[PDB]
Image (cartoon, coloured by chain):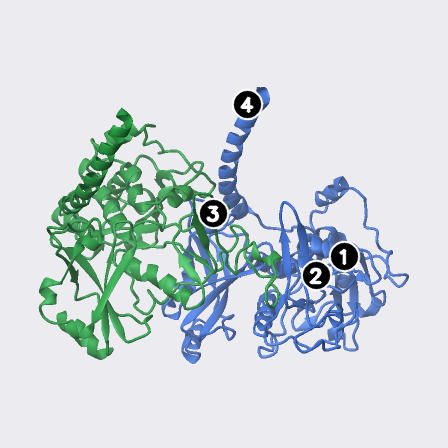
Chain colours: A green, B blue
Amino acid sequence: SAEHVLTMLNEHAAAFVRFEATDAAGASRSKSIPAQFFEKVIHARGYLEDGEVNAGAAGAAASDIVLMPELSTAAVAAAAAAATAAVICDGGAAAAASPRYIARAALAQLQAAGAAAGLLSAFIADFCIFGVPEVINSKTISFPASTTAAAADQPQEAAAGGAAGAAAGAAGGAAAAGAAEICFLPEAAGAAAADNAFTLRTGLQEVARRYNAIASAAAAAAAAAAGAGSHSIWDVGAAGTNAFAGASGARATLTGAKWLAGLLAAAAAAAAAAAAAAAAAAAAAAGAAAAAATAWGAAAAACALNIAAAAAAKGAQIENKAGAAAANPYLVLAATVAAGLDGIQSAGAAAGAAAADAAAAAPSEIPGKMEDALAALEQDAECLKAGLGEAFIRAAVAAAKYELENEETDAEGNKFLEYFI
Amino acid sequence: SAEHVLTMLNEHAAAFVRFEATDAAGASRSKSIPAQFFEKVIHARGYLEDGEVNAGAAGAAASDIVLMPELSTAAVAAAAAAATAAVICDGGAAAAASPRYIARAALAQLQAAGAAAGLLSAFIADFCIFGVPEVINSKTISFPASTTAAAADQPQEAAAGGAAGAAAGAAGGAAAAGAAEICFLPEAAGAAAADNAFTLRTGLQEVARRYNAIASAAAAAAAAAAGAGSHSIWDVGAAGTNAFAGASGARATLTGAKWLAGLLAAAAAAAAAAAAAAAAAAAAAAGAAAAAATAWGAAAAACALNIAAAAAAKGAQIENKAGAAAANPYLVLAATVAAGLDGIQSAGAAAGAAAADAAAAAPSEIPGKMEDALAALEQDAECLKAGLGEAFIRAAVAAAKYELENEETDAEGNKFLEYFI
């Protein structure tokens, strides 16, 4: 409803409006203008901008690209110092580097294949909080550091009125409140971590800053302790009903086992979005509560693909663990679905459920070389990177590459002369 | 009453609610969500969470455990910066590491044995207060330090308007107010230090912080002075009457003497909860007012198990001293009862009352070796660690042990090669 977005500007006396998007790495970004600019044309043509400001979105002969706001997603920007609103956007011209538009192609493919009509997932991702982080690097030193009032290191230190004597312990601080709070509760938001992830990611920081603290999503923010995992639950449906419920193990079904077979096969490549930083590889390292074990079950807690068993058949779902909060939400939402969408077409199987010791059966996969990982990427190849291009990416990246190669070929020309002398 | 907890959210306009619990060491912990989530389902199913956040509550194949709030225990969280409420919980799945649920088993055993119908105890525990504590350790130094406006060290020091000249002395500061205050007085709370201990432990800190100070429960917070003891009074009843009143010494009775016999025998193991830190062992060290003398009486003030003599027979009770505020309240409440519950079944006796010099008669027990302490633990053994398991503990701890043993066996494998060269 264009009419609803226009009446919200009067209903909340909005002086300005914020356009919002997300990059390929996984961070949200925004821009803003006075509310007076909003008219019928932008509801059909968006906002034209110069894309040369971003090294992978345009080129010098094509310095015009479009942000495209939407008319079912507007909200009051209540954390601001003034009466304002916010609106998430797709990006276009084109285009095929906008993560939200890439995620929408997986939803279109789910419907076009006739396998179902929608997807019913949700997330339970963790985060970290601090008072004085300090992280720097140079030609002579490199160190991270951080602290918080709850930290197990503080009760030995002095303070302006003495220590509280009430700090947490190592893996011993499971006493925090919820739902952490105002970016889900007043909206009663409920839906999947596509659009909803970024109001949470900005909200955690903005609320902490308004309480003289900060928040982060660093997957391994401290050693010898817990970290910011991004565990989730996953489900499929059509005509108003669940499609993973049935009479196989832990109340799952055969199409659920085929989605699991796709997820198990794709785990080595889904990690490129779900574990997009070295901190997530550190969080996935060996330990008594790790989640790198690419297996399924309903009791082996370390296995990456639990079954969410329930008394009501409508609540029979799966539970994915193969990632951390350093990830890109839209690209995780795309990649985990792309695996399931072809597991149902290969008709593969998840093998037997894990109920032994914490790791093995399946794990497997597996061959132990980069050459075999590339061979898998070129044989299946169908649970992985499914559909689209990439034409927009190579067009924008070519403009940057031509400038870089012109500087590098002149530098190589000088270097060759400096080798012939 | 589920209805009463729901109407409190309207009556006090609560925006959020705080779930609360306690760990095995003895510290309270909490989490929170918006009040809008409260519905009929959580009153019968609690809140599911990932237990891998705590190294002794779940495992990777069983990453689902339940917090279980209650519907007779809700209160307004009046110390908060907003309109909110708080609710203590049990924990389950399972389970048998939740201290409050472990304490409830002793109350169930008291009733199931037919010995009585309830327990009528209370506590008088001490605490400490400071302005600038400083405590740190490294590879090169180790030191504690602290101070407060009342301390005997301050009257020789300068201040921004000169010294007050009104500090206390060593063992000479018995002039503090009571009931210390707002976590007992406005509730008229009265009942035993099971549920009531943690509102006091958080309240002392929160009130001190709101007066630019801090509070603590360190049993031996400073040398050559008093410390944070956790002395208590104990009683038993059924059909509306006291069951320790009678015609033996100091108006006690024979079942009271059998409870005392159990307590005297169990003292060497009840200390594992009542003196859970090295500061409590330091508080129990030799001196003119120590409480380590495992004996009973009504005049020998150092004896660990006084009789609370009274003019009214309803007030004839006992008084236990064998602990300090570093303890875990729920596990002390369990262990001290577990001793009494089998003293009445062995039909043992407390020997004669102490009225001589400050220590001896009984003390005794006693054999002077760890082998004999272990022999006692394997012969009685019935006043000690009575009932339950522990199945939940070993299940969660096994998941942690498998990760630890996988890292340690690889390290030992490398170490063996480094010994064979």
Query: Which percent across, then down, holds residue A34?
Result: 20, 73
Disc 4 or 2, which lies upstream in sequence? 2
Of pointers 2 and 1, the one earlier in the residue sequence:
2
Where does residue B116 sit, x and y in percent of width and height?
A: 66, 64
Q: State the residue at coordinates (72%, 47%).
A: B380
Q: Which residue is mark 1?
A: B284
* Mark nearer the viewer, 3 or 2: 3
Q: Secondary structure at mark 2?
A: loop
Q: Where does label 4 land, which residue?
A: B417
Q: Give percent across and percent down for residue B421.
A: 57, 19
- Of A12 and A257, which appears nearest the observer? A12
Q: Which residue is mark 2?
A: B221
> Marks 4 and 1, Cα distance to the nearest angstrom?
48 Å
- Report the residue marked by disc 3: A143
- Tell me the kind of residue under disc 1: Ala
- Give A369 or B277, whichever is nearer the viewer: A369
B189 relative to B76 in the view: left or right: right
Mark 2 to mark 1 CA distance (whole Å): 13 Å
Q: Chain of mark 4?
A: B
Same-chain status of marks 3 and 2: no
Q: Which residue is farthest front? A: A421
Mark 3 → mark 2, Cα distance in angstroms: 35 Å
From the viewer's perspective, is residue A47 above or below residue A97? Answer: below
